Amino acid sequence: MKLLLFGYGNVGKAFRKLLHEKRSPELNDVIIGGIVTRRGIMLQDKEDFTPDLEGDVFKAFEKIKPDIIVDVSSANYNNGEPSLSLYKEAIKDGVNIITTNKAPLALAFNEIFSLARSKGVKIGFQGTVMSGTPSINLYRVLPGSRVIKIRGILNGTTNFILTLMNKGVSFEEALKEAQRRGYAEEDPTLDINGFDAAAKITILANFMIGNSVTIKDVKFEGINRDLPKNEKIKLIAYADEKEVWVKPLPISQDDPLYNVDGVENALEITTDIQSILIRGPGAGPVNAAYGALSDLILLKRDCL
Amino acid sequence: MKLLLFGYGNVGKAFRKLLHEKRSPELNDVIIGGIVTRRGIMLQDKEDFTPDLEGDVFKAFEKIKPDIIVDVSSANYNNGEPSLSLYKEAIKDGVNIITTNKAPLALAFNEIFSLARSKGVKIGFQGTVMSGTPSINLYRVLPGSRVIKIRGILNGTTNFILTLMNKGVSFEEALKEAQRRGINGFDAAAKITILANFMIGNSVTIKDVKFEGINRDLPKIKLIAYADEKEVWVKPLPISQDDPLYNVDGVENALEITTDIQSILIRGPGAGPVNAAYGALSDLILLKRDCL
Ligand SMILES: [Mg+2]
Ligand SMILES: [Mg+2]
Image (cartoon, rainbow over all chains, first blue to last red; front, side, top):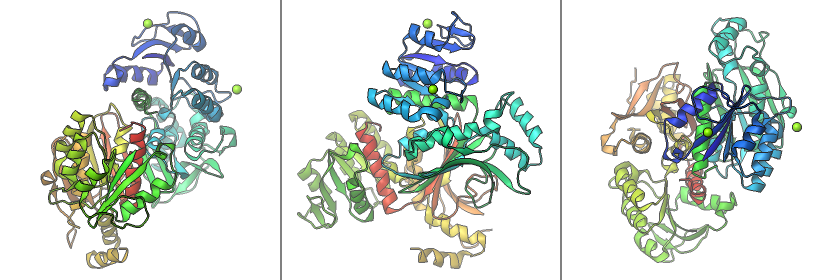
């Protein structure tokens, strides 16, 4: 089982590590044919990235001919590239996709999944929502339930920030602390302007409801310190059959989301049978990589 | 695929209704070979139960020769019978089991599952713990992680009664108020036994659980089930405001799975006929997909 690993920051390295910890027998035949980053292509499975050749992901894909692409690269919300056209071409080749990269599914879910459905190709995408906390994969074990509405906290960075702000730390200081900790990048736009949460609710509305939505259809706002006096604020993502949105709201103590704090995330799934809530870490590179690994083993069991 | 439905109270009625609701392409070829109750054997798929033959689940097993036994009969916590010997005969014939009956698994998990593993037979058992809220099946989507500890609220009723007590409506009134919407912590004890066998690998039976139910004058207390490699117990505990279980009130279950990677918690409605039947139905589809 040959993997092409696209991306190698912290999530990529954590993925490589988990895989080599032999946590499952389904993973005995798994090889890393290559790893591709901004700095080139490494045709070897080593802990540190040293490129062997110049080139992008398309060149790597053509040279390696993997069985699976593991996509842990950064979300590009402008157009989803190069991941979007990379997924389309791989699926046509009967190449499976495992992704934590939100952008292509947030932009072109129906385009991706129809084509995957037509070619019998499997897409792991647990890592796109709530990292290693089953969200996509939770729904997989709820077959035949019809989802009515979803509601949750879907962004680790802004939750950690709004948690600190509830404790008397300023927006600015909670920002710098999220960055020192790695949860937020030097440019935290996607988190703080709410793109990330909006991407996630888009994916969930697509997969769980069956709404044919893109991130364009989502009315969203991020965080900024013009927020309510004496409230615990949460960046709430919502979707049903009719609407999908993300906004920071005052949370009351009776809400099952009130105490979902720090990098913790939660999802409330209301179905025709029941209303369930799941909670766990929303960020952390080990967590995100574990989402991808969960998909990998599931793919190996033919359970995607 | 031919089912034998064992039990036809509310859960079994709810399962038969769900199955014909055309919920999945996986369920297009599924037929009910027969339904068994304590009054006998109906060899037909109908809404109303009327016996075609007298005789027990063993006679029905022989007469129908099904592919799958769906067990939604009531828990017999004395000895797990007839389900426990039924399951053994089933597995030995290559017949899969989907169950909501806690008792056989709570009393003799290792005996059932060693047999099934050696014979290659899949068991669906989601409905035994937290009904239709993925618990057993949550851990199925957590592959390659090691479960260090479990914690939770595994009985809706006791949880609901405890909710009113701390709120003001103390033990006497809360007892009576509960019955209007309708205690020793036994039911949580069976559920935690199953969770400990499957997720931790502790070869526990119900007799190993140190369990105590609610008292009259509790000095926010919750009925808490817990397991790890060392211990399995159910104690009423005053729970800290920092707990993610603190807000789990009413007729609700919740489960905190702690692995080497992460700590996750799932919460849903406790136990109900449609919920319970949905757990069995989920397992059925999962089994059809070969994902058990
Ligand atoms: Mg190589
Ligand atoms: Mg485009």
